[PDB]
Every structure is written in structure tokens, then in C-alpha cells.
Image (cartoon, rainbow, N blue to C red):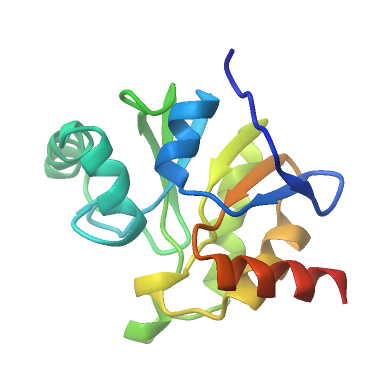
Length: 169
């Protein structure tokens, strides 16, 4: 069945978290929407984007390249909706700020606001990893900003454990 999310920990009325690999979750769950941790040029060579793209056998990148060549880049804090290929009905490509590259952390709020157009989403923690932002902060912005139902996948067990502890303080 679609959107079969299993084994999540409910944080708030609409935010859930699991220590899991987002690619494997997308396969198990068959979600309507998977969120990609995109950059403005939809170049999915690394991070979560690379994992999602590889799981689509490069179909996501081919589609994204054609999109960008005609439609131009996204903005930091922005999004677009493309195909979910084999992983979901839709992929919501969301650009969080890359604070490793000096972008404004305040754009992380705008980034999460993109989730509010979709009733339920499977998602990574925005601006983590190669984007360099503090994950405890990202979870707080998620909780404070997203109103629709978001199921967060965090594969690194140590990070998952610190996030749950932070939420429960």
C-alpha cells in the first residue's frame, strides 16, 4: 500500500522520525512524495540526492538536466516537483541552505515551508551532510515550520539518537 510508514517515532502531531535509509524507506513505504535534498542546479552527484538518483538508475538526473536547461535553476529555500520515478509518485526537490558554502541558515525555514503543499512526505533532514548545517537546529525548524505529515529518515544511528534526545529535552 502507498504511504505505509512503519516503525516511526512520533515527535509531534505531524513529525515522525526513524533510523533508516531513505532509499530503502522509499522502497518499503511507496510514498506519494519523497523529498530530495537538492541543490539549485538539480545536480545529484552527492549526498542524499546521489543516493536517490542512483536508486532511479540515473533517471532522476536525466529528467533534472532536461528540466534545468529549459526552466532555469531553483532558488535556495525553494522547490520543484518532478517525477518520483520508481521511488515515489512525486519527488519534491527542496533546496536547503548550504552553510558550508556561506548561504544564510535562515533560508532553512523557507526550505521546510515547501513541505506544506503536500499532505504526507518521506524526507531527509534538510541542510544536513554536505550542506553543513546543525542537525539539531534543522529538526527544530522542521517541527516549527512543517504542518503536514513528515516522516524523517536518518540513517546514521549516532545522529538519530542525538536528535531524539534533543527533541525530548
